[PDB]
Length: 203
Length: 203
Image (tube, chains in turn orange, cyan):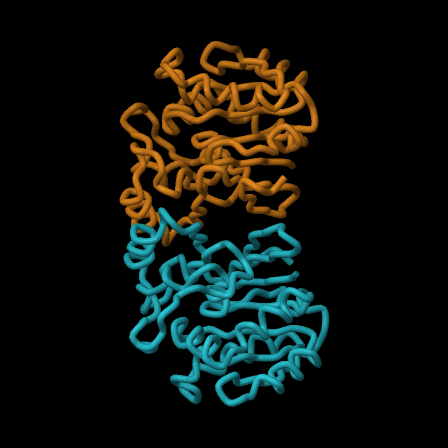
């Protein structure tokens, strides 16, 4: 079981995958699909020599979700609106498909919202991403691929998520949940239980 | 270079040292040396089969600090008042002695205040430990054995350091310093650059 949970990507993503073909799951950002600078995430992976296989879960039946995830060397779950991404994952039902494939050894890279849904819950980022985008979302449980609750952009370097609200997130969820503050540039390299916390320079 | 930085100890401390003899540096808690439950830290290491060599830096000339640190399998820097511990380390001058010995491969275990002084600064815990205990302490720079700024007891489970002030610490120091929230039971196993974040169960 291999996870690479980044706040906003990491230079060793390509080495983590160990291959060239990565399924790119964009649904977290479907709410502004063709908005300027939404492609910056795909350029980061492409700049490292990865060829991306787009896999929009909202527009794919689960049989084809299964077929792509068995023809790729890894899967990448892009950032965006965390609550809408879990709405997709639970409604589509690919939450079971992706989780099953990840546990069989398919390496999983998370970025922002992709890193949070890998953990036990998305409730700890409700001061970061709006929960109102999924008003019919009852259960906030994540995929459970990791027990660590990633809080991305922990430096306060994004205007939508300033250090005041990251602090509010710690005040609100720090007691029950094992919060992990990730700054942009950092990533969690998780491999068969061992959790390595990497900075930018670790490659 | 081997560090094990715990919030409040970790079950694998003995395995980290790889030997039986550990120099126990108690000065962070000299301000209440014989106070009830101050010995709980020494029992934790002793319960794991470690024989502790007490090394109070306030009462030891640097030549003997050097001699003990060369006859032990590792060094343990106990919790207490972070600002008084750095006052000791800088005034005694053992900050250079310990740092030199750690870089030569002497394994270093930090607990609370011992884990914070290993990093770049102690200023990020000034809402946790009082800086007034060292009014003549000019420079807040740490030992620099790690670049990660450990914030211990991050769960808010200690009455003196509730989740509100850990949140205030993130609001106050989160932008400049690479804050690492450690909950009691967690520890950072750092070995030749690689930083592993361990939970209680990782042993």
